[PDB]
Length: 97
Image (cartoon, rainbow, N blue to C red; front, side, top):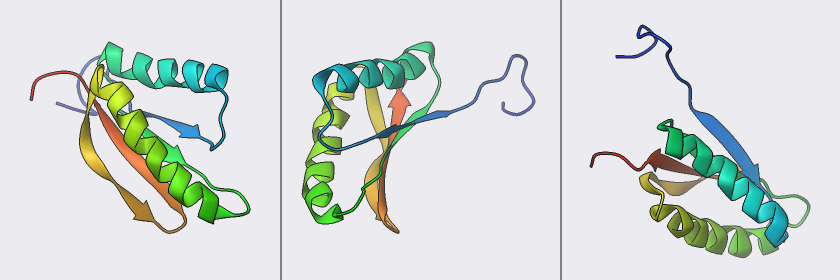
């Protein structure tokens, strides 16, 4: 049931950045969640700029904490992985197993 249903839906993505302020980190979290709440899929992507080293250890520890922040309103469908020079995570809507 896809690309041929009725209203149909589409997964959304939200980018994040290191050293993000609580304010920006909150609204962003809500957005990502809003996508899950409705019932749609959502994935996060961390982009580094300049010295990725610092963002590497910090960007990693982030997804981990962030993933949990969602574990309460979502679940992990695809463990994070390193791709090229960017990090990406996949969050699934809190529904079924």
